[PDB]
Image (cartoon, rainbow, N blue to C red):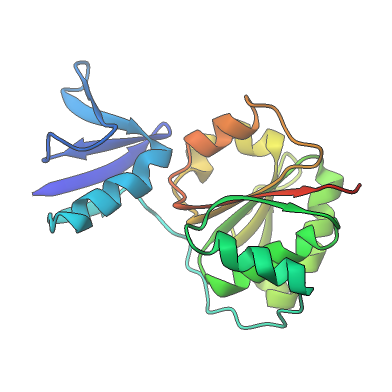
Length: 206
């Protein structure tokens, strides 16, 4: 029987020996893939009607969100385009409409979400902004506090260092790229996360 599980930011696959992007690891005697390949491996099992056990994903229990989705027309335009693959980047003119489309997305897919923002300061803002979902579901994971709520905002720093710990607890990954972040900060965090849904955010202005 097919089974997968997570560790050190990688997916271990037992059973199927022809799983995509999974390579054989002679040290362990197993196939292994970077955690972000999680989604592909899943769609591979399901698509081929293959039976499997998911010991990889360990989703934080998240409620059904149904709050005030107030966006601008162009803001709601993109959201719907990103909703097709739920794995892309969104460029927005505004900037407060960035922290807006994000909110919208979270609300649509009521799944555990990690929000990576540079600087604590910017995290503090996002927390109190996520409150329109329930202050009790909003957490912060940083050098200041390491809490894991269904909606946790983290700093590029804290997220990079605890990739092991955050990697399999979220299904939706959001990057608040303020002027964009390093291909060693940004890229590295993404790669070790199993999160099948990714949303990168940038504000042309400010």
